[PDB]
Amino acid sequence: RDDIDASAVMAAYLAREYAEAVEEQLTPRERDALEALRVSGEEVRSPLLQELSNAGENPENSHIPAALVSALLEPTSPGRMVTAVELCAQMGRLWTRGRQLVDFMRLVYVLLDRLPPTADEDLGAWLQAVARVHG
Amino acid sequence: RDDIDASAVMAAYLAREYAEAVEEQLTPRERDALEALRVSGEEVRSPLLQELSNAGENPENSHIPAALVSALLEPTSPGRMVTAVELCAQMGRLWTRGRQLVDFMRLVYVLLDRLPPTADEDLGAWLQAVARVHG
Ligand SMILES: [Cl-]
Ligand SMILES: [Cl-]
Ligand SMILES: [Cl-]
Ligand SMILES: [Cl-]
Ligand SMILES: [Mg+2]
Ligand SMILES: [Mg+2]
Ligand SMILES: [Mg+2]
Ligand SMILES: [Mg+2]
Ligand SMILES: [Mg+2]
Ligand SMILES: [Mg+2]
Ligand SMILES: [Mg+2]
Ligand code: NA
Ligand code: NA
Ligand code: NA
Ligand code: NA
Ligand code: NA
Ligand code: NA
Ligand code: NA
Ligand code: NA
Ligand code: NA
Ligand code: NA
């Protein structure tokens, strides 16, 4: 049990150091948005990928999340944008061991490369929508 | 101050959710490795990039970190590997606003794509070396 998954340790380190750095700069309303994404993150977006990845410890099937993200961001809606983000976070929770890190990074890249310019406005719109409906 | 940097919020969310997921699975010795990377992370690897990025709020000059990482991992050493990781973390702390997220993701990709297979062994070697020298 002295074996070290270098890829895993390095990814965890960099992810936390970047997460904490960004969080320190966020505005109060940006912080409210982050919490809302956490709350929405507990609603499983793809139970099929939850079960399939519950199995294992092909690469063709590791592409399904990226294809779904791209499909969600293709004439899109704020809801589909948040849904794409939440799907990525949820695959992150399953794709923790070293050899899966490659698939996870592609997934996030597909996400952030295919966002709309209206993302800043749409996320503000989504936040106020969920707040007004649930508040 | 109601404007929302969607890219920033989404990146922070995903980075934290992935960091916490990986951390929960890490072995005790893998956890010791993560702390060691934090300690080493307080030793600025490139003061020049620290000063240059202290300025601003070109893309040619945002490529310098990636080129340094690739140079460090080109017949490499454990020390250069850790140094590459620490340089990435330190650029993460400067590259927090939305339009810089693109550069940061490339940087990390260059890092993890150019690792050696001996990374798992080398990180174990580095950990025991720093422990034996400082313990
Ligand atoms: Cl989940
Ligand atoms: Cl409310
Ligand atoms: Cl730093
Ligand atoms: Cl010690
Ligand atoms: Mg601020
Ligand atoms: Mg899912
Ligand atoms: Mg596919
Ligand atoms: Mg374990
Ligand atoms: Mg630096
Ligand atoms: Mg260059
Ligand atoms: Mg990438
Ligand atoms: Na507020
Ligand atoms: Na599905
Ligand atoms: Na690996
Ligand atoms: Na889009
Ligand atoms: Na709603
Ligand atoms: Na231990
Ligand atoms: Na330098
Ligand atoms: Na942006
Ligand atoms: Na290498
Ligand atoms: Na040493």
Image: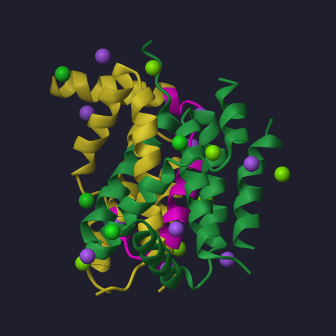
Chain colours: A green, B yellow
Q: Residue furthest top?
A: A1
When asked about the image quadrant of residue B88, the answer is bottom left
Instruction: Name the foreground residue: B21 vs A41.
Output: A41
Quadrant where the N terminus of chain A lies?
Answer: top left
Residue B114, visible in the rendered structure:
no
Residue A64 place in picture, x, y as percent: 77, 49
Look at 34% across and 20% down and name the residue there.
B28
Query: In front: B42, or B32?
Result: B32
Residue A22: name its quadrant.
bottom left
Judging depth in this view, the residue of B61 and B106 nearest the camera is B106
Residue at image coords 33%, 28%? B31
Residue B102 located within the stretch drawn in magenta: yes
- Residue span colored magenta: B93-120
In the picture, measured across the screen, residue B85 lies left or right of residue A49, that is left
Q: Where, quadrant-wise, is the C terminus of chain A in this rendering?
A: bottom left
Query: What's the residue at 67%, 73% (across, down)?
Result: A114
Count the numbered circles shown. Answer: 0
> Residue B16: percent from the left, percent from the top?
40, 51
Is residue A85 in the magenta section?
Answer: no
Residue A132, picture quadrant: bottom left
Q: Is residue B5 above or below residue A35?
A: below
Residue B85 placement (x, y as % from top left): 41, 49
